[PDB]
Length: 4
Length: 240
Ligand SMILES: [Cl-]
Image (cartoon, rainbow over all chains, first blue to last red; front, side):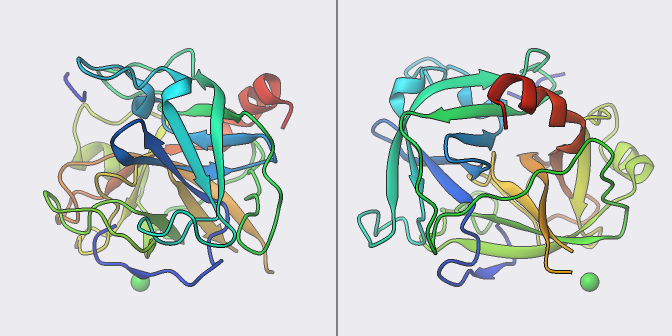
């Protein structure tokens, strides 16, 4: 989903 | 750490500070043996401009209390020989957010440098239990780090509650710890540091600072990598  | 207080000298002697070349403190870690640290895999992922994955670009400070006093008595500075990131670490979801860091030369235990005990694979930290987080992270979301190591007491959150507060973001490797009313939480720069469970006079590492939705917000407790599940992986990869 986009944690970086 | 948001909502915490200054730690006493020597109070968390397993807490380590990891500095990246030319940047100062980036992440925490914990001392588990003379040669090995536990930290968070996501701290060791490259970006443009810096290879955080390169072990040679890190310096670990053991026995540190104040970031402005890194040459104080009792501080041991070490380079890293290698970084073992968990094989299943996923950098888009932060599942399996744990890494093992090998020091180039062993630490010497002292009044300021001591290991924390690992939990065995059967160890449970039940929902409701009060435990501690420590670090040099920001003391407010979007703020600046603390010079003096901070500590805060927080509570383990039920896993179903955790899943529902952060939907589609929680895996079984993660645990929410904090308060549903916010106020006390870890924050940016605490990543990779330990949860310390003080429970007789024994202290166990419960988990690793990983991520959160902002910091100290209500219904958004911090998220930590659970540690018992990794006991055998640690043993196999480090001997510890
Ligand atoms: Cl309480």
